[PDB]
Image (cartoon, coloured by chain):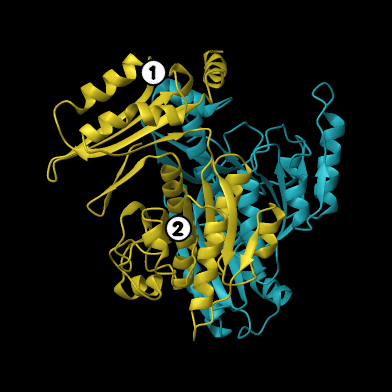
Chain colours: A cyan, B yellow
Amino acid sequence: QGMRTFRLVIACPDRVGIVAKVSNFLASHNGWITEASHHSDNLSGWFFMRHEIRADTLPFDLDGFREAFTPIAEEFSMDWRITDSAQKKRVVLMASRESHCLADLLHRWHSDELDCDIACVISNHQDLRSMVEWHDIPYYHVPVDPKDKEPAFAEVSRLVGHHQADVVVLARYMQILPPQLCREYAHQVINIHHSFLPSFVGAKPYHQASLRGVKLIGATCHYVTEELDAGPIIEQDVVRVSHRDSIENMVRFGRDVEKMVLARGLRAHLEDRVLVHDNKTVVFD
Amino acid sequence: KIHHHHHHENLYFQGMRTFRLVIACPDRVGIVAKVSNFLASHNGWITEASHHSDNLSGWFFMRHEIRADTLPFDLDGFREAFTPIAEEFSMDWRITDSAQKKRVVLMASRESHCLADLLHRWHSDELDCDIACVISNHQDLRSMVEWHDIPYYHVPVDPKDKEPAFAEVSRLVGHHQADVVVLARYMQILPPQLCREYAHQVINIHHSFLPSFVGAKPYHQASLRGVKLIGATCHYVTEELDAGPIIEQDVVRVSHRDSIENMVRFGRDVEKMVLARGLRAHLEDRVLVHDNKTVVFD
């Protein structure tokens, strides 16, 4: 149950023989499949698949499996990858002043639940340094001059680059990202937004929810794209509120939802379970 | 622009000191007339009022939050001035001061998820209380507790002779003058005197949706039964095992896709959410116990 696996993730145009062709390849090579997920989107004519395969009994290393599988990938014009479960992804966390999401992720990492390397935390304030330095994770204070954002932008993108980041996570980071960053890290920048999108975009979404008098509020984990708050949704959830709940109390319930939803989305990402197509996700749980 | 003005207005009135009057008594026609008249006569402005009748036992429950500074006396004077009404109506009652922090003793064994959640809420000023200390049967959680400058007492349990451990937990809880003892996944037997001395002041988080799956390894039990939801139960500890008054419960969906280790992991999130919610209700004097059940005024 604590065994090394390779994960094969595929999105491609639907073809009749893909399951046959991939299963023949895997079975003939003693691919012990521990997990297999499938989805067809008949309206766009696309197919999606994910396999977890025992590494030790497959007669390939990671590079050799990639090479051996390339002829099938090319035959079916696949968007694909193979990863090694024992190869930790490098995560960069970004945070401003709110600590709830950051502390949650750091606890999960510290307790060996969240399987990854936290490369560093970047922040526009000094507030969260102490909690981050307790974990012996580098903490970087990159303050943002609102009159001149280019130096802040450059230093963020340099630090991300230096740490060879595989994922950038905005744990309630409230400033504008360097515009190039989501272009270079396409579907690798994960945000937690504090409303149940597409409702209540913009500033103070709990205030907006209170004024509209909704009976449930929520949070949305999504990939960041060039268009504000419009990126592919990875996970959402909600919590019930009533007339009895002041804004302060809604914000407080919201923190718990934000924490949970970000954690679920990041882990799905880390485990190579999330695929993006037509600005939407398939999430193989 | 209307959503920012609402941001200022909401901050403007926040954090004003209240007294909390909490009553349970035999239900009678004139209880509310008499209490509200008493408050009105002393110019007390009630900013929250929650009433409940239990028609099967014929009991009445109420909680009023009153602006402390609209009244002409301190907490002691309120108690003395209110005693005649309490006696007339045979009330089980109390008055607390929102500015007086309750002293919480936390207990933990090896699992850190509930304890870290509560410590974080405390440190970020969300959880209004003083954490007097953490008592633990192991040394594992020392480092995280001591970072917060909270005392940590390692009281190892000798499973052959449990009395030296029991005596020390009781001494420590007494020395810190605890108002609440919270078992943040503490897995050892409590001193039997503790839940009698601290009646309805010892709060536990149990890792099953009670009354299902009592005993050892509740997640393993759920997996074998093949249920499609699992949960956690926050409850007061009483002399009878697992049977105490339930404060809060919640659940998370599971399916055939989920291994026991996945279910245990989902469990940790339900446990910590449910414990936090239950502790907060208690700290705010929103929980009244009657007939082994709770009224929770939200």
Nearer to the camera, A21 or B121: B121
**How many marks are shown on the rendered structure?**
2
**Rendered image quadrant of residue B60:** top left
Asked whether the beta carbons under mark 1 and mark 2 sit within 8 Å of each other, the answer is: no
Query: In the image, A115: left or right of B29?
Result: right
- Camera sees residue A17: no
- Camera sees residue A29: yes
**Rendered image quadrant of residue A53:** bottom right
Nearer to the camera, A46 or B6: B6
Q: Can you say whether B147 is above or below B214 in the image?
A: above
Chain of residue at mark 1: B
Q: Can you say whether A9 is above or below A241 in the image?
A: below
Q: Which residue is mark 2?
A: B271
Residue A280 in the image: state x and y as whole percent.
52, 44
Nearer to the camera, A135 or B71: B71
Q: Identify the residue shown where x is 58% and y is 50%.
A: B131
Q: Which residue is mark 1?
A: B44
Q: Amino acid at mark 1?
A: Gly
Upstream in sequence: badge 1 or badge 2: 1
Q: Amino acid at mark 2?
A: Glu
Q: Can you say whether A24 is above or below B298 in the image?
A: below
Q: CA distance from mark 1 to mark 2?
A: 39 Å
Residue A253 in the image: state x and y as whole percent.
48, 39
Dot 2 crowding, Cα within 10 Å, few <14, some 14–19, many 20+: many
Q: Identify the residue shown where x is 40% and y is 32%.
A: B20
Nearer to the camera, A1 or B54: B54
Residue A4 in the image: state x and y as whole percent.
62, 77
Badge 1 marks a residue whose secondary structure is: loop
Badge 2 marks a residue whose secondary structure is: helix
Dot 1 crowding, Cα within 10 Å, few <14, some 14–19, many 20+: many
